[PDB]
Image (cartoon, rainbow over all chains, first blue to last red; front, side):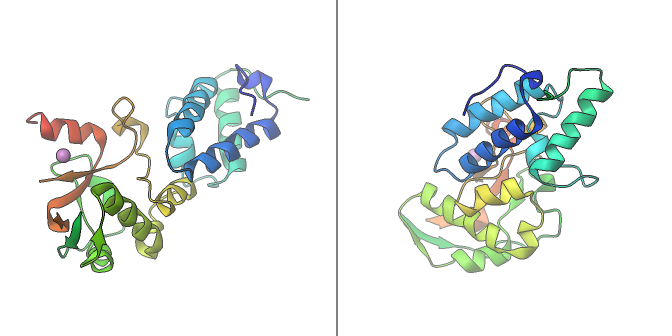
Length: 87
Length: 119
Ligand code: NI
C-alpha cells in the first residue's frame, strides 16, 4: 500500500494494514518485497529491537498485530516520541 | 540432487538457543526421520522441505512466533533476532561441515560468517 514517512502519519488501523502486508509477504516465495517493508517498519517505529517486535514478541504481551501496535504505542509514549495519528 | 540421510539429534524446548555459537544447532531427530531417504532436486529444495517439516512439528513450532511459523510453512528460514543478523542476511542459515543431515546445522548469519572466517 502507501508507505508513510512517519508514525505520526499512521492511524493505528493503517499501521495494522502495514503489518498484515508484511504477514502476506512472509508467505511469498522470496523476501525481496518483505525486506523493504521490514526496513520501513524499523525506520518509522524507531524501536531499538526493530523487527524483533514482529518476530520475537515479548511474553508479557500478545503475539498479534494488536499487541505489536500496543507495544509500539507504549514505547513511543514512554520515550516522548510522537504517537499514532488520531483521525 | 540426491537423497537425505542421517539421524539428527534430540533437542529441547530451546532448539535454536545456541545457533549463534560453535557449529550451531543440529537437525532434530524427529525432523531427520521425516526427511530420511527422501530425494531432493537441490539443496534449496531440501531446505524448503526442512523448514516445512519444522512448522509441522508441534514441539518445534511452539518455539517460534506466528510470523516465523508462517515463513517456515512455505519453506523459508525463520528470521533471526535483530542482534544475530549480518547485513542482508537476516534469517537462519544451514551450514555444512548427498544431503547428510548429520553434517548440517542451523546457524545465525553472524555466527556463520565467523565459522568460515576461522573464528
Ligand atoms: Ni557454512
